[PDB]
Image (cartoon, rainbow, N blue to C red; front, side, top):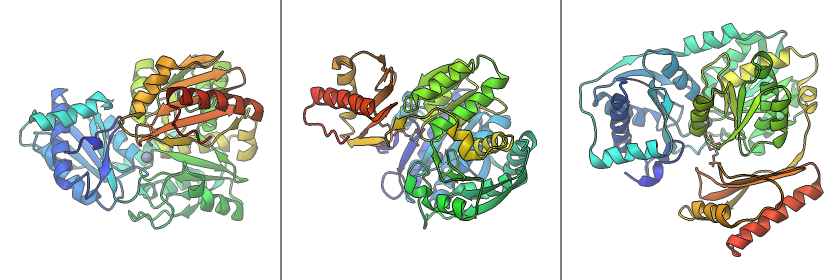
Length: 455
Ligand SMILES: O=P(O)(O)OC[C@H]1O[C@H](O)[C@H](O)[C@@H](O)[C@@H]1O
Ligand SMILES: [Zn+2]
């Protein structure tokens, strides 16, 4: 199998090219072998709404079966519903077949074994098992499990909206259309659906709410229908994007402000995790409410590991993955996060625009990407960590280099999903933003004078 599909956070490839039916089978063999090595014969399996779903999921399941695993096949579900299965069934392993927000031909695997979401060396260990033929052999079994009604009821029964809201819901023709509009209505909303038919051709915008262009239709519909809120889901439903009643995009780090206030209010001293891409304002806000802010690495599986290590009650990252442990299970879930948001907003007499605008804001950049090479990106970061000078500031090298200054911050790190450097900048003023950008421009040039500095 090609090494490139074994990534830091998950497995991801292109069907017909780097990901085939046979590769899915052997990946299932590897996962079932690791699950058995951890004392867990029971493995839940789910798939999203992609065209290659049926082909690859059958092979994934047979690979698990051929280890001697007992598979619980939950069919086509959102990613968090597969994570839910792996938390509420007797078995604590699960595999989701998904390509997330990528174009139609992409697919992949998000993997939980004996309660732990695999990352980094553990994902490589699967590749290595297949190369070594270090694989279990047995006569397993498959049972059908219809889990979505239990998930739906679990959420509905714990959410208490204080008044009705009208909400536009954009599923981007991804799998969130199997539940999100239905569940949000059941909470006590009117729902205007946009692209809520599941269609793996993604004939409208790709289900990727991190790009403003994929929210254009949502924003227009919110305005036209005088809705209270707009929500957009990514293809597999583990990410959510939010738009206010006036069309303002609320990025996930400011959504986390509202959620952190909520969670900490009932849980004094609670740890709250955010990634290195998130606003410094969220850090002061968590501390102010008496929570413990914990900055960590970008990446869903890395965040989940950190939540286990710290006992954090809430985590989020700038990509829109939000992870509730309080009243929940600790995994990322756009659908559940949407419900928690509606709960909070419904208890406020103000519109969603004013709830969010009340929080301090700074000037920030759209995420910047510089294309380098896959085989150099980590070395550029290592060179910065060894060589760079940042002036006076609080330097964090847990994921790339982030420097927090009195009036702003900057970040450079390697993407683990693409061959690029990722940068973000934020400051109280344009003048400071430009000062920080100049520091980073010059430090990149000091490592390699030839690097593009397109910011
Ligand atoms: O910045 P990157 O390493 O490219 O990762 C950006 C995002 O990629 C995927 O969407 C993962 O599911 C997210 O957890 C991560 O935040
Ligand atoms: Zn996703």
